[PDB]
Image (tube, helix red, strand yellow):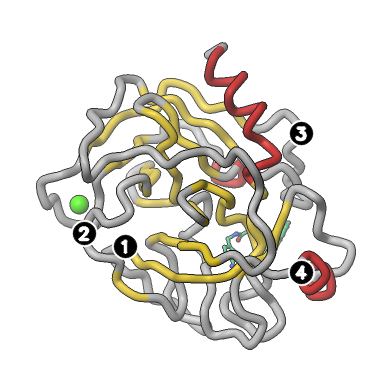
Amino acid sequence: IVGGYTCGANTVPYQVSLNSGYHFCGGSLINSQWVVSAAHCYKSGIQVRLGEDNINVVEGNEQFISASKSIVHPSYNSNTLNNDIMLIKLKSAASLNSRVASISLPTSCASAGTQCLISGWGNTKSSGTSYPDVLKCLKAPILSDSSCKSAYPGQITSNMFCAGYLEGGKDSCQGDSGGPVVCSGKLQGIVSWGSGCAQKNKPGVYTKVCNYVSWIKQTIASN
Ligand SMILES: NC(=[NH2+])c1ccc(CNC(=O)[C@@H]2CCCN2C(=O)[C@H](N)Cc2ccccc2)cc1
Ligand SMILES: [Ca+2]
């Protein structure tokens, strides 16, 4: 997260870190057994880390749970990141508490102009690299689809939306991949892609979760 702020420990209790020896992606807890992340975060051997603030220090509220299965969206395209969503099942149910909590799936999509909270442990620099160890947060509005497509002509599908600031300076970044965009209490986006980070006229692009709620609900009920 570039241009954001330190969230505060466990103030985003649905935020998970995906760990394969190191943090490599974010995700969102949607019930005690399931996490939503980005398909571009797919790999084997995932440990889900819940209750995290500083990902390099055991602070006392963590739950570390291995994934038992991962399900990449059936239509994910790795060349374009269309359908950039994946479900991860926990081998044992998380113990839900005020620091480890699920985020509600959208009943309805959100409209342009709605403010959202984006969070993660990704790079905080718009040029170069600095990775924080505590969770960072950013308030950012959904941008119009026309400004999104103007920024990225020929690349935006109906399964994507842009959010952030066309002037630059505030954005998500590498390492935030797969983490949440929460608007009005619903998981509306997943950190997906963009050109650089926090660059002028290059806003963040996010998987449009509301298009996937039927698939999520049917997939978790059958797995
Ligand atoms: N909001 C942002 N500026 C931002 C940008 C990037 C990321 C992390 N996501 C990435 O790094 C993804 C993974 C594959 C390549 N990639 C990218 O974002 C590429 N830079 C652009 C690209 C390549 C192929 C298809 C779609 C988009 C997270 C946030
Ligand atoms: Ca920790």
Q: Are marks 1 and 2 in contact (CB under 8 Å)?
A: yes
Q: Amino acid at mark 1?
A: Leu
Indicate if the residue with disc 3 has its beta carbon within 8 Å of ligand 1: no
N-terminal of the pair, mark 2 or mark 4, is: 2
Q: Amino acid at mark 4?
A: Cys
> Where residue 13 sits: x, y (%)?
30, 48
Residue that carries the numbered disc 4 in the rendered image: 148
Q: CA distance from mark 3 to mark 4?
A: 22 Å
Judging from the image, what secondary structure is the residue with disc 3 in?
A: loop
Q: Which mark is residue 135?
A: 1
Q: Which mark is residue 9?
A: 2
N-terminal of the pair, mark 2 or mark 3, is: 2
Q: Nearer the viewer, mark 2 or mark 3?
A: 2
Residue that carries the numbered disc 3 in the rendered image: 75
N-terminal of the pair, mark 1 or mark 4, is: 1
Q: CA distance from mark 3 to mark 1?
A: 31 Å
Q: Categorize mark 3 by other alpha carbons within 10 Å: few (<14), some (14-19), many (20+).
A: few
Q: Categorize mark 1 by other alpha carbons within 10 Å: few (<14), some (14-19), many (20+).
A: many
Q: Amino acid at mark 3?
A: Ser
